[PDB]
Image (spheres, coloured by chain):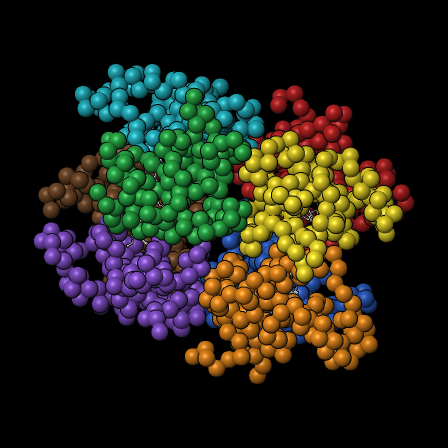
Chain colours: A brown, B blue, C red, D cyan, E orange, F yellow, G purple, H green
Amino acid sequence: KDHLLKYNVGDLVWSKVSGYPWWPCMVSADPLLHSYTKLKSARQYHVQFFGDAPERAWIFEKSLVAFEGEGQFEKLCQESAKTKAEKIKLLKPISGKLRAQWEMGIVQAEEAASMSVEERKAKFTFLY
Amino acid sequence: LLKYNVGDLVWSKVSGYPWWPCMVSADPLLHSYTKLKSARQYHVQFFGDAPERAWIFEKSLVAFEGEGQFEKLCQESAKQTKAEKIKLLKPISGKLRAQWEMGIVQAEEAASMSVEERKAKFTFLY
Amino acid sequence: DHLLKYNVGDLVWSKVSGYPWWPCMVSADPLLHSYTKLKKSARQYHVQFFGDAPERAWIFEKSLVAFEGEGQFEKLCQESAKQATKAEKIKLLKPISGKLRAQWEMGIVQAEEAASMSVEERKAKFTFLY
Amino acid sequence: LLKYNVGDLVWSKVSGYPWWPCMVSADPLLHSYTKLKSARQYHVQFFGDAPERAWIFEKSLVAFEGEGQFEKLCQESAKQATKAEKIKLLKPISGKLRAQWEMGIVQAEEAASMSVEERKAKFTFLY
Amino acid sequence: KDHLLKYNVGDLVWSKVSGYPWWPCMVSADPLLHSYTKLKSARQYHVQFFGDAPERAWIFEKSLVAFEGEGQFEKLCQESAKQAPTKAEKIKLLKPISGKLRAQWEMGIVQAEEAASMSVEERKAKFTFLY
Amino acid sequence: HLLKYNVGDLVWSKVSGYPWWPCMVSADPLLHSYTKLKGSARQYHVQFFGDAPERAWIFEKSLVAFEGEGQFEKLCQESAKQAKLLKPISGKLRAQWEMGIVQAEEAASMSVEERKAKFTFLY
Amino acid sequence: LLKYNVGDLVWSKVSGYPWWPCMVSADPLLHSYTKLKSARQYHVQFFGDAPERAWIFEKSLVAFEGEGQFEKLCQESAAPTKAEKIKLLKPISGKLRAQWEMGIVQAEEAASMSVEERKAKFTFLY
Amino acid sequence: DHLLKYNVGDLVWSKVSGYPWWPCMVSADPLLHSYTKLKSARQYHVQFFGDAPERAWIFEKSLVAFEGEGQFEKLCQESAKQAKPISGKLRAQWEMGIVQAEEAASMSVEERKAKFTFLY
Ligand SMILES: O=C1COc2cc(C(=O)N(Cc3cccs3)C3CC3)ccc2N1
Ligand SMILES: O=C1COc2cc(C(=O)N(Cc3cccs3)C3CC3)ccc2N1
Ligand SMILES: O=C1COc2cc(C(=O)N(Cc3cccs3)C3CC3)ccc2N1
Ligand SMILES: O=C1COc2cc(C(=O)N(Cc3cccs3)C3CC3)ccc2N1
Ligand SMILES: O=C1COc2cc(C(=O)N(Cc3cccs3)C3CC3)ccc2N1
Ligand SMILES: O=C1COc2cc(C(=O)N(Cc3cccs3)C3CC3)ccc2N1
Ligand SMILES: O=C1COc2cc(C(=O)N(Cc3cccs3)C3CC3)ccc2N1
Ligand SMILES: O=C1COc2cc(C(=O)N(Cc3cccs3)C3CC3)ccc2N1
């Protein structure tokens, strides 16, 4: 039973990886391990990072926030900012290649959000 | 409120072919798994070493439990044209028998799994 | 391009001897990169056959009809049968079965979804990779 | 009544990169080639041996004619730029990036010698 | 663990499928199920059919013969025709292959003989068909 | 210097039950050779041109250098005299044969190096 | 008489990287899994979501039992150079920590399998 | 083709600014289908050998016929006089290239084209 977890396959989330901005993702099954959640005492979910160069990872629930839209990003940065060096880095706006790919991810996540979970699973699940 | 959902294992009947082990899946292009053609259809994937897919009517689908169902499925389809009946009861041979067998082995391995895991393992890429 | 009857992305029905009128999309040859040619004296267009098992060919304009929807198929069969050899007519009127019926149906579903789209969007969604 | 269409060859400017030869294309997933963010963007593919793609603002696009435009593009982007930004913009590309930029230019010039339909059939990167 | 069976992954065998000639094969793991042998009371092995259009199947041990070379094929046909109780089956079994199937059978033999000239490890790395 | 054909050469190939088909001499994707001796009698690895490409090891006796489509009629008439063969191809096979001819004629208009880079089917 | 064979799980040390979960494999082009350079090397595949491969010296390989070995591997590797030691003891972060973690998860799942099954499941396609 | 210094399948060392002399093979552009061009100065399209293959159009002046690994030391010393040993990921991939190039060198041009031409 999946009806008992906070997130399920196809759910849109923001993921935080140290040294990267909060990123638009979808919860998905590991292409090899075929699981989407696991315990490490602490729950993790397998996610896919939206964009033109897709990546994937096992991210802790503590580092996930349900995706509603782009408007959440500012508060996510301000809350994550609140190490002295880490704060100055977190508040700084993204540039170059990473800004383009982050933008590409948001466009994909917002398109995915306008869909039922089944359709977005069939359209946005990245093949590996 | 639908009889089947993505990941459900079914037997599908296509005229001129034996009842085949399948899984209900989303269409790779249309991203839907069910549609109305007044009469409901489901998109399915045919299990085997040479996978295929199709939009099959609900009337031509039966929930998959295991291989043991096949004999009754043949006998019921045969009872439901004199030439059609003799063809339906005849056991499969050669390439088709091997691929049918391969499908059953895949479907039974899929059946031993939770729906989420079987979707992640057995959904054929297109 | 604005001077030819058909262009890349246009939906057409194609007739190949021994097959039913099939839902297609005019497309560029994956290798030759042309979508129309003269065989020049007679014009041909490269088409992709819609379905779960996609195929492609260079089809003569005489064997192409602009696709509007499934409702045209009956008249296409009846007109092709009247134009046809006594054996050819009986074959043309006979309804498709098995694997071919399923794939023809799959093509129709794809063609009708493609028809509900702007040419640019349908080229980006329905052009089969080769 | 839009400035660019699918298959049009453009130069794109991405912060930290030289003006790059591109072709306007449809997003492989979203199937659109232009969108509004009040400000118009176009989906482009970056030419070269390691292809990439992005949604670039119209203000950061210039119609591609040939390699000869690049010098003026650098000099105009430098004049429009922060003292540090100008010194960086005028500096010539080297190593892997110079090779890939060169590869893109060769592809873009070969694409330019073709009718829009033929270049779409040959140079649209598969994703 | 895998030291007790007649065949192992990478072993070259001839496989008999009803309606087809004895075909050059390699024993291999199922690309999805990751097993190379199973019991159905009767043992089966997963094989890949050599040729330009590769295929795969689960074949019963009774329908497998260790591959030494092309020279075995004549005796295999001869033994198959003698074991076939049906008169029609025998005439079919002795008939030589033609067209596309003859070419692909030939292609398989060429691949199998190349594979035979290699150590098991090397032939697994070169001839295992990707799926 | 003694072989009639080399990688990239355009040939017509005859396979029993099929019309003379537009081909190109190529290396085997696995065996990496383009010619061999079966036994006494030389074979060449070829790739059949068309929208559904295939490949095979064909005997030299079943190969004829490709110049163009105009050769096909004489090839049929000569194969018929040496022997169904005279009957014209239809349906799917006629379309794919036509597709092969179009590919072979485009390949013929190119230098050997360019045609190897463009028309060698990936496997 | 070789220490490792195709399918064996090992930890590999590449200068500037943490000890990484690998599996011994045949080179996809050269079809060999071990060679001499005098000194023996093995072809390995680095486990993770972004797989890589390399020819690694036997001296830089340690048989993989599980994640619990990593701490002692770091402490033993921690190097005559003073700068090298401080770098080696420092814990991995960001993208590399995620991919290292992904590799461990894959290596531990591979370890729970018979050599034949793990070669069929975890040999990365090239 | 019989008139140029290099042809498709020939093994060469390539020099790209900021990289060590790298074991390569002359090949046709997967898109442009040419293997040499003039830019007054001749270039050849090459593929860099290794586990992560790359390709580029390199000037003839930056190419040297590949005989074996033993040439590398002199190539560095000559390139330094005209103007540090490789480590980590790059050292491994360079090593992987040498192994591939030396295997390719032991083969006839035809066979090495069929085995070592990287698909794109
Ligand atoms: O198009 C895209 C989508 O994915 C990206 C991930 C990354 C990216 O590097 N990461 C970190 C990773 C952890 C595990 C693997 S990758 C994620 C942002 C946090 C960078 C650029 C990307 N571009
Ligand atoms: O490995 C496999 C799995 O799929 C098959 C389908 C078929 C097969 O031909 N069909 C009919 C089809 C209808 C739509 C497309 S395909 C299905 C059995 C009913 C034949 C062999 C197969 N082998
Ligand atoms: O999914 C599909 C779509 O394409 C098909 C083509 C055919 C099919 O065979 N044809 C004939 C062809 C012309 C040249 C190559 S293929 C077309 C119907 C006219 C059969 C089944 C198909 N199923
Ligand atoms: O062969 C190529 C073509 O594309 C490249 C893009 C880049 C490259 O990194 N960029 C920035 C990007 C923004 C969005 C995704 S990529 C483009 C130059 C501006 C670097 C090298 C490349 N090499
Ligand atoms: O290149 C090849 C190799 O494989 C083939 C298998 C077949 C072929 O059809 N078979 C029967 C099969 C059973 C299971 C799947 S396929 C095998 C010969 C017995 C036909 C042609 C082939 N050509
Ligand atoms: O597009 C194409 C090209 O290749 C074909 C080969 C065949 C085809 O079946 N053959 C026979 C073969 C022998 C070895 C493998 S294939 C060749 C014509 C003689 C049929 C249709 C094709 N369509
Ligand atoms: O998912 C993964 C798995 O492989 C990686 C290798 C590397 C990685 O860069 N290396 C060094 C290499 C040497 C030869 C080629 S790659 C290995 C860790 C030592 C970095 C990140 C990875 N992420
Ligand atoms: O496996 C490999 C082979 O190719 C490489 C190229 C490079 C590499 O970056 N280059 C520079 C390039 C110029 C054009 C595109 S790439 C070449 C060494 C000079 C780095 C690592 C590699 N690893």
Q: Toward which corner of the image does residue E61 lie, by quadrant?
A: bottom right
Residue G62 drawn above or below residue C71: below
> As drawn, which residue projects farthest toward the front?
F1
> Nearest the camera: E15 or G27?
G27
Q: Is residue E83 left or right of residue H112?
A: right
Image position, residue E47 (x, y; %): 57, 68
Residue E103 seen from this side: yes
Tell me what residue is drawn at x 62 percent, y 43 percent.
F1
Q: Position of residue G5 (x, y in %)?
A: 37, 69
> Farthest residue toward the right?
C86
Camera-side residue: C12 or D83?
A: D83
Q: Nearer the viewer, residue E93 or H72?
A: H72
**Residue lying farthest bottom?**
E41
Residue at screen point 59% across, 64% down: E113
The residue under the point 60% across, 49% down is F34
Q: Quadrant of the N terminus of chain E?
A: bottom left
Measuring 70% from the left and 57% from the top, which residue is drawn there?
A: F40
How many dots with numbers?
A: 0
Q: Position of residue E68 (x, y in %)?
A: 60, 72
Q: Looking at the picture, how far across and down is residue H100, in whole percent?
A: 41, 51
Instruction: Judge from the rendering whether residue B126 lies leftward or rightward of residue H68; answer left or right.
Output: right
Q: Is residue B116 visible?
A: no
Compared across the picture, whether A87 is left or right of G110 comes to left
User: As displayed, is residue G126 above or below residue F22?
Assistant: below
